[PDB]
Amino acid sequence: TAELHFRCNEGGMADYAAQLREVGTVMLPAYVAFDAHELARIDALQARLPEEPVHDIYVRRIMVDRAGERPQLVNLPHSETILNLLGDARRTRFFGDMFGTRAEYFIRRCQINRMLKDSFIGMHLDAASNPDYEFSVVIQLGRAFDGGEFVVHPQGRPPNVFAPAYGTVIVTSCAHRHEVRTVRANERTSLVYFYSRHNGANRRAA
Ligand SMILES: [Cl-]
Ligand SMILES: [Fe+3]
């Protein structure tokens, strides 16, 4: 009956980490985390990747993280170039502060999701793929679309609704169920990746 809609956080690091802490999700405005020319590069690079259906959602894998296995680079060489940006010193410091820990974090899984009109992502928990995922990061590469809100459903709270634009970045804790609502026009393209302090094998049973 009631849903809490969020705009991009207009503050700084102290504000970003506090919203992630209290709310569990924060949306950063373009182009704080990744500069526009960097997103332009990522966009040119991901196009070169092989696409597979997963048919109203098409997925371009960069890094896979199968049950019982350790994270694996795939679709070389352009996957690694994208990953190099995601894990460079600027981003490592940026998300290190964002998460509020000195501990080393690893990017375990990473892919481009291309969602066509009338696609959606039903309710789920990222922890179900890997119980050690702590945070998820989503970069919006979709130039223009309707619908497609990223919705988080924390236990005993109103849903938190995020409408993302090109260049925005959502950071969210994997402790909350979440979903993407129906895409209502053109297509919605996002780079999604997952952070864990564990770099060993995925403890989800295969
Ligand atoms: Cl910029
Ligand atoms: Fe998810």
Image (spheres, grey):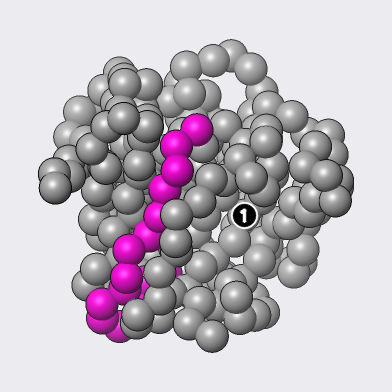
Q: Where is residue 45 in the image (x, y as percent from the top left)?
A: 57, 70
The local crowd at label 1, few if under 14, some if 14 to 19, many if 20 or more residues have their Cα within 10 Å, is many
Out of 176 and 63, give the one closest to the viewer.
176
Residue at point 78%, 53% (across, down): 66
Q: Height in image: 2 above or below 51?
A: above
Asked if residue 143 shows in the view, the reply is no
Q: What is the span of residues highlighted in magenta in the rendered image?
A: 175-190
Magenta highlight on residue 189: yes
Q: Height in image: 149 above or below 188?
A: above
Residue at point 30%, 83% (across, down): 186
- Residue lying at the far top in this picture: please name it: 102
| Helix, strand or loop under label 1 | strand
Q: Does the residue labelled 1 lie within 8 Å of ligand 2?
A: no
Q: Where is residue 47 in the image (x, y as percent from the top left)?
A: 55, 77
In terms of image quadrants, where is residue 33? top left
Name the residue beneath numbered marker 1. Answer: 110
Residue at point 32%, 70% (across, down): 182
Q: Height in image: 115 above or below 138?
A: below
Q: Position of residue 31 (x, y in %)?
A: 30, 48
Asked if residue 15 shows in the view, the reply is yes
Amino acid type of the residue tagged 1 in the rendering: Cys
11 to the left or right of 77: left
Q: Height in image: 1 above or below 11?
A: below
189 to the left or right of 91: left
Residue at point 51%, 68% (across, down): 113
In terms of image quadrants, where is residue 20? top left
Report the label total.
1
Magenta highlight on residue 31: no
Q: Position of residue 154 (x, y in %)?
A: 36, 35
